[PDB]
Amino acid sequence: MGENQELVLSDHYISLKRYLSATSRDGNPKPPPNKARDKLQRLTEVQFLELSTDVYDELKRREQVARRGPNAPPETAPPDFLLPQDNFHPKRNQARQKLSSLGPPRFRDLATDVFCELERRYPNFANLEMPLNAS
């Protein structure tokens, strides 16, 4: 254990890589035809972390939904969007709702942009490590 924002983004990076890998063979290193990393530079690091967290949170919520997809009762069926809470600011809640509203292609692009940004910003993320699946 330790305290490092890089480690937090490392988990996000790994999660994004697995997410992208699970949704794409990754035969194209640059999926989008257009790029604009300068757009992501129009925000602060904290805002960037907030966006990274929002993306991460969206990813885990979708995974939970998928897990509770088949062979799951409707009583414990999760929402198709993040429900608002007073613990979180309403603007942030709306932002999260927008992520849910966005379909997979747009979201995938967001994931790709964040993933690429993290890889470019942290070149050492290209030399982290990945887990293995076994059953």
Image: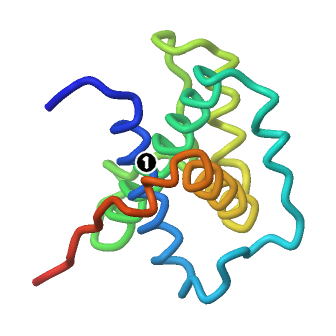
Neighbour class for label 1 at 10 Å: few (<14), some, many (≥20)? many
Q: Residue at x 65, y 37 (%)?
A: 97
Q: Position of residue 89 (x, y in %)?
A: 59, 12
Please name the amino acid that badge 1 sits on: His
Give the vertical position of 21 relative to 104 (above or below).
Answer: below
Q: Residue at x 69, y 27 (%)?
A: 94
Mark 1 lies on residue: 12
Residue 92 lies left or right of residue 70; in this view the side is: right
Q: Position of residue 7 (x, y in %)?
A: 33, 38
**Relative depth, front residue between 24 and 102:** 24
Q: Residue at x 13, y 82 (%)?
A: 134
Give the vertical position of 108 relative to 93 (above or below).
Answer: below
**Relative depth, front residue between 133 and 124:** 124
Rendered-image quadrant of the N terminus: top left
**Relative depth, front residue between 59 and 71:** 59
Rendered-image quadrant of the C terminus: bottom left
Label 1: which secondary element: helix
Q: Position of residue 43 (x, y in %)?
A: 75, 25
Q: Residue at x 33, y 49 (%)?
A: 75
Count of labels in the image? 1
